[PDB]
Image (tube, rainbow, N blue to C red; front, side, top):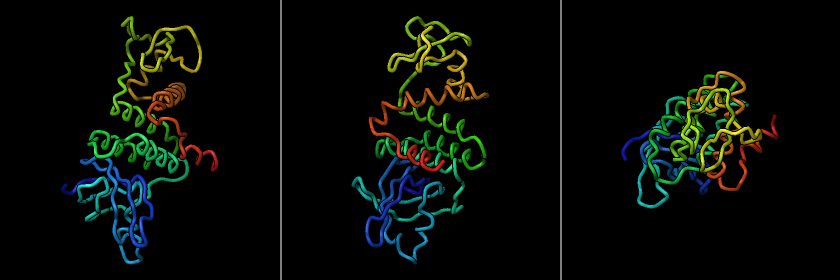
Length: 231
């Protein structure tokens, strides 16, 4: 490109004067960007190149690592505090683990906007926002779980019936009650990404954990370690 919207996932010192950015861009997908000069007292880059700051970006180069040409912000935003800060950090960690470089995910970018607009305009609780983004993300990664029909038998899910999740398998009606067990009502909540009560929220969390695991593959989440130690 081309001017395009973006958010910074991470920012680190790359040299005496420069930063290395890991950026989520709307049209190019995830890219790594060097910001020359952005460490220097006398650059405006510095204040702008933070997570959760909406950006418009131009950058160039052929390699995996591109070079930032210019960046524009409006809100030098930090919309995000305490539980909601650690939530945003969480979402950026997810994307870091999960997003392949330089694949356009433009719908996902919209989902990330909405999730950010949510985390900004809430006090208690971030969870519906979070669960909704996880599911959009799983969608966009292509996990293809059917929430609304029993796997194999093809039978419609009933609110009050119980079901077991099989990774890679779908949901099947079951009276085995354990940590893979969901309620037809909970499956409907998941399919709608609406969670009107604590019971569906709870079960949403339990599910998205499981479904995300095969994508995080192996290492635990730092941002969880962060919440633990602060709360």
